[PDB]
Length: 330
Image (cartoon, rainbow, N blue to C red; front, top):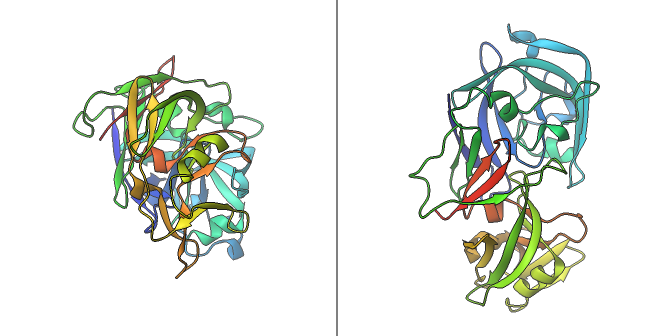
């Protein structure tokens, strides 16, 4: 079996992407943020603190005939941006683009942090990293992809994110019409629970390609591309007036600039991120200082190939016995 669901940017800057997911019987549709950087399926629910819910669609397990409380199980998660959520756990039928998993752990949010409350369009997260990162205690739970894997035609899912446009998440198959050229596959380390791979280098605009190993994660749940200080400085050095601002929290550039492209290597292949994808608009409404889409990973401890990089490609997340990542131009 297979699944196919459309993913849509939550705003004019592609800050996050939402994909409709059906939970329970009769179906309750919630717009979840598919996150290849975490392994918890958590939702805003009837159990979420009323002052922390601001316009979200909530999951009401009492109205679902297939919902069952996973007695005693709790979850507690905190993300790289400092945001967090926690609560109890139910099992229920979950469908993504026609692909159904019965008895999926659906972690019901009791408490959410301010960042989640502020995103009225995001009803929760659908974790797609390795199940070893799942926070459910005392019995660790599997992701939607882990649970669907045996029913899938091929144990894969693909991310085809759009630039200021909707995209697609496919499960179980590779759409040969969604990309040009060939897919270049690269090794994945599952040691940290992430889709962790090694980029073979980079180029800035029409500059020479620099062959250097850059360990990083393919993360659909991170908006920007986070790379080592050396690489980020070499990129922003090509933009007149660009600087790193401690007051803003990263690199900013004059909104009047035309950004150069950024190429990253995947084995012997190249993925080009157009300059427009790196523009995240004014830092504040009306400002002439614009936020950069390429930021330093120095404070994070890991390089992150976020949406800025992933949307420039058709990305295959191969969950076979030996997991691999495929990148193709599109």
